[PDB]
Amino acid sequence: VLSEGEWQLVLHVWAKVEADVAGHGQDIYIRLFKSHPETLEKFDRFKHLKTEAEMKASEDLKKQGVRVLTALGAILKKKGHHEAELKPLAQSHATKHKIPIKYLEFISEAIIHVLHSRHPGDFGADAQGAMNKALELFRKDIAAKYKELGYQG
Ligand code: HEM
Ligand SMILES: [Xe]
Ligand SMILES: [Xe]
Ligand SMILES: [Xe]
Ligand SMILES: [Xe]
């Protein structure tokens, strides 16, 4: 369980992401696909992209990144009271997309890396620890829903 102070560290960096969610999403996807290329294979619409240049130029990838970060932002804004928000996401990611918890760990890593790079003013050590705790909680709760849904993750 995060403290209110921890949630505020999470929300204060998220406020900066929201200056330009699209640009943040592009950086996060590029980082994910570069660091863990296997994750790109899960994307029917994007697995053909060969280079960072192609990734940057993809309007559909940009739009997907906006969807991801906005869905995650809504979850973070619930400050742990995210049962309703997690249900459709867990179901689609377990059953349609088939995304293991390991890959959620990878995207969490990419999120942290991009925030660390872009936002040293709001992503010092305490803020990074708070964001890690929030993402760990997210993954814990997704993992529990995965198991309810019959997916080992
Ligand atoms: C922060 C964690 C993530 C969030 C909040 C998130 C959110 C979303 C949302 C909102 C959608 C569209 C609605 C849906 O189908 O549920 C989506 C689609 C999708 N997600 Fe995720 N996602 C996350 C992580 C991942 C990861 C790590 C992968 C694969 C490695 C993945 C694979 C996909 C795929 C393949 C789609 C369909 C994309 C398309 O329309 O072409 N997701 N995700
Ligand atoms: Xe993203
Ligand atoms: Xe997810
Ligand atoms: Xe995550
Ligand atoms: Xe969360």
Image: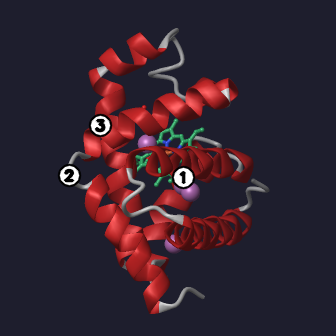
Q: Which residue is located at x 55 percent, y 72 percent?
A: 134
Q: Which residue is located at x 61 percent, y 48 percent?
A: 109
Q: How far is the residue under mark 3 from the one under mark 2?
A: 9 Å
**The CB of the residue at mark 2 lies under 8 Å from ligand 2:** no
> Toward which corner of the image does residue 33 lie, by quadrant?
top right
Foreground: 50 or 16?
16
Q: Quadrant of the N terminus?
A: bottom right
The location of residue 152, given as percent across then percent down, is 79, 56
Which amino acid type is marked by label 1?
Ile
The location of residue 54, given as percent across then percent down, is 40, 11
Q: How far is the residue under mark 3 from the one under mark 1?
A: 15 Å
Secondary structure under tag 1 reads helix
Secondary structure under tag 3 reads helix
In the image, taking residue 106 as reference, residue 50 lies left or right, namely left
Tell me the residue that label 1 is attached to.
112
Q: How far is the residue under mark 2 from the one under mark 1?
A: 17 Å
Q: Which residue is located at x 49 percent, y 64 percent?
A: 124
Residue 139 vs 107, above or below: the answer is below
Q: Is residue 30 visible?
A: yes
Tell me the residue that label 2 is attached to.
19
In the image, taking residue 94 as reference, residue 74 lies left or right, namely left
